[PDB]
Amino acid sequence: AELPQWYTLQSQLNVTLSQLVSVTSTLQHFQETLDSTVVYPLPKFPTTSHESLVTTLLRKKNIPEVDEWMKYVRETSGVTTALLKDEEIEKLLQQDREITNWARTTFRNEYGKHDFSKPFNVDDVLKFTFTGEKPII
Amino acid sequence: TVMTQEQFVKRRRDMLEHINLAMNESSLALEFVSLLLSSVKESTGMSSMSPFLRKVVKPSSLNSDKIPYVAPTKKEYIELDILNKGWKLQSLNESKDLLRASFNKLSSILQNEHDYWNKIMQSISNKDVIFKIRDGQKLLAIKYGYEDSGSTYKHDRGIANIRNNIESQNLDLIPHVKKFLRVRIFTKIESEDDYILSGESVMKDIRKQIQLLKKIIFEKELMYQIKKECALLISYGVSIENENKVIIELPNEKFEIELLSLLPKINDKRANLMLVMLRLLLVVIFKKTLRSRISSPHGLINLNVDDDILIIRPILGKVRFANYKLLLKKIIKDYVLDIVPGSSITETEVERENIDDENITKLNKEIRAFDKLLNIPRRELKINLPLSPNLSLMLESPNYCNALIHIKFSAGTAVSFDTTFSDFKEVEDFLHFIVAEYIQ
Amino acid sequence: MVQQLSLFGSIGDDGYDLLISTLTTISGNPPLLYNSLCTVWKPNPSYDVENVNSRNQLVEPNRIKLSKEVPFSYLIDETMMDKPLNFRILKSFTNDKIPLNYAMTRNILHNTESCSPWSLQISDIPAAGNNRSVSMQTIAETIILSSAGKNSSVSSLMNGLGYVFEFQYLTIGVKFFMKHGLILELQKIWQIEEAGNSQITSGGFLLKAYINVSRGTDIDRINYTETALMNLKKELQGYIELSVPDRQSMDSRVAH
Amino acid sequence: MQPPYIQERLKSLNDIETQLCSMLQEASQVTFIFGELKRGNESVKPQFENHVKQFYERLDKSTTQLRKEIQLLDENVGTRLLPINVNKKALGQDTEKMEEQLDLLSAILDP
Amino acid sequence: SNQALYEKLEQTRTILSVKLAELINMTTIADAQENSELAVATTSVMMVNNQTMQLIKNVQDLLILTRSIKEKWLLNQIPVTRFDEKQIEELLDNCIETFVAE
């Protein structure tokens, strides 16, 4: 009922994000030879009393929320495929990549434009005050 | 914006349900990949299994085979690229909204903080002292107490928390009720009856609040030291009524020094004067204690009551000595001036009276400025006589509520007396003897 | 028999006023200007003495010192009457130039009837027990109230004890009576000689933080004062370094 | 009231705070105009260049201002600051109270 | 304490100087490399949930540092007549004479 103090939970959120980016880096670096391995169950698996177990075990049809949001994202891009020919999309993505290159070199040149005691001896004075010897300098 | 408890618990429950779904999907993904792992390894995948799953299905029950290597087509390439562009655009819009909202919050917070700091500057001078304090948050507390400026009062140190009130546009001090003490002068009619009042003393901003808090703690300290002093004067008609109001009983007047919370009378002026005497005498105690702490290594940590307070003793002794002088003048008149054929009673005040440093000399001259109030009241009353008898009466009060008469008499027709009295009937019959024995 | 638990340090002349402000904030007491002319007397070399005393114990010959407060009119060089007597006076005293020359000190000593009060102090070497973090010294002190007679001069009086004059020094400083009975001095030291005055603390102030305790057997009181001194060293830590001076420096005994 | 050096440091720190607040204005503007030029628009290109260069120069100004503020804090540690940490004491309040009460006497005695 | 503020400001500045630039930089389309929808989704969540509010924490840490040094400037300051004795004595004598009313 009481939340932890915010720095620890922020650290947990950051390390979970780093863990998931490690997950997708591992999976995307091993992209192929994972598209090439299809999974099927075995006769040792109970496919009569536990086929409900296996049908939601190999499923690649994701939850409706993520792909309705994905299709919402698709139409908000401002460009689609259903009324444009594919080479127009290819050249639009090419010029968008050129615009990314221009923007990152603008950031690069804007970033590169700028830069990123002792006056005496206490013992000798005390030896004077107790004995009379002058402080030798 | 404002957010409520039900909104808070609703947001908590919905993020809890979303993260429940997150861990569910991640756990089924992990449990699937470990199930497929257990077909070929059986060692490491069994660790991350669920006990219920191992109960219901045995491991090594899945298998995979290789479909041939395929080059992905350009149609899904451009599909993924256009979806990437859409996802990037949506993320950029979300980032813009987040940054705008956080800027609005930061701008409001910075406006409040800069108003607070400008109030701090236009409010606090460098003469004042401020230090951090915890509740556990950081608060700036100003020390307005007199304890480091001569006071010895550990019951209530003057510490006030400075709080910012944006609505009031001013800084308010929270002491970490306005009760100023006032005096009442009750005269007595010439019938030995109940006392009627004849006079009484008179009864926002950051600096006004600091001054008011210093005034409040000063009056509380003054009333505390008065109450401590009255126990030594209980024998002289001085009574502590209710630990916040003391009464001074006089044969013709009555002073009521009361500490209370919340038209021109004859004795209002004297009441105001007595109030300023009380405050100045407390200041004199502060100066003497500060001098002792400065000039000595040990200093005065506590105040001795009969030696170091002297608050109501001097001001009571002034009027008490006035009454004693009136009684002595009446007695001298009756027993000499009503008897001899012409003499004048003449009163003259009689007086008797290294560490060179600016601070010590300043403290000494400040204390000696108030010597004429703080000292023992003394007066010598000398009566001339026709010739050659000489007679003098030095009236003094070594205790501020006491009475000592040091009569000195000599005559040429010889005798020479120097005697001390503590009462007035002895003066009466002594003078009655002297006038008939030598003057008559 | 006063035990003196003391710590010592040094500052430059430039950091004097900052230290005055700092110790004013720490103490809550303003600095007080003080001075004392200290004349140190050694035993007469022409007198054959014994290593033993009236008891059968061995005693080394020890210099003893008299001190008194010289009035500040003798220390103003006809330029500082307008300036009041406070801590700002010590900013001017930088060179060897002091109005107190040798002849005025001889006038003080030879009293050219009744003499001013003096303070005779005898101090032995501080203790060698390496478990105490402050310089603990024993000072045998007495107060010469007055004098009279045909030889009322304190020089002839000290010659009466068998003691001859060896040297003298003038110290002027500011001191703080702090909390828990701690005295914190901050003093210049000038040696007075016939050849001319010499500033021993050349371009700097000698710092002495001492607590006087009457009973040396009150180990609770000794530990309390030692903890107070270590505390004061801890607030001053980093700014100024307070340390136990060498015991060979504080040994006032006559070597031979 | 307060020393004018404290005024300079207070106003400079408030200026630093406002500059790093407008840091977020211009970062939001940069990501906004990048979003619109990702929609196919090209007329917002020089305004995007203006926003990014303004972002970098205001970052430089805020960081250099904070750096010299920390330098002035660490430099005046002996000139106008305490070299150690110690709570100050309110001194001279008794003299102020004496002056206040004597002014009250001068008021009451002479109308 | 005062030394730590130096490197604190230094590290906040050196991550503010590159974080928005790398945010713009990693939105690069190529056939780093995003060969699946997973890389696209994780990039578009990590930018919003990792870069923008880390800029927020950066400017909030700068605010905390400025508030701390402002409090240090305020608190750590070093601290820096009308009635003469004869006038006070005259005032006291007149005041007592009026108060007693002999």
Image (cartoon, rainbow, N blue to C red):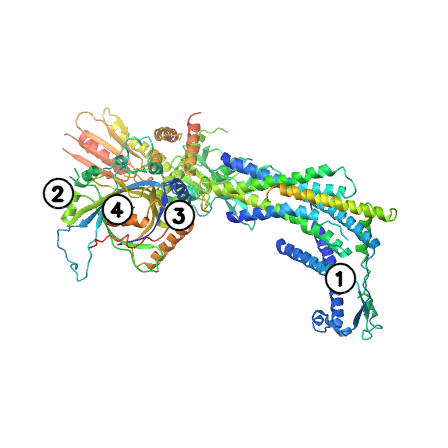
Q: Local crowd at mark 4 within 10 Å, few (<14), some, or many (≥20)?
A: some
Q: Nearer the viewer, residue C178 or B102?
A: B102
A132 relative position to D84: left or right: left
C22 relative position to A89: left or right: left
Q: Are marks 3 and 4 in contact (CB under 8 Å)?
A: no
**Quadrant location of residue E98?**
top left
Disc number lying in front (4 or 2): 4
Question: Which label belongs to residue A134?
Answer: 4
Q: Nearer the viewer, residue B260 or A97?
A: A97
Query: Which residue has dot 3 on it?
Result: C240
- Across and down, in percent, residue D35 comes to 75, 43
- Across and down, in percent, residue A84 comes to 87, 46
The three-letter amino acid code for the residue at tag 3 is: Ile
The three-letter amino acid code for the residue at tag 2 is: Asn
Above or below — where is C192 with respect to A51?
A: above
Disc number lying in front (3 or 4): 4
Distance (Cα) linking label 1 and label 3: 64 Å
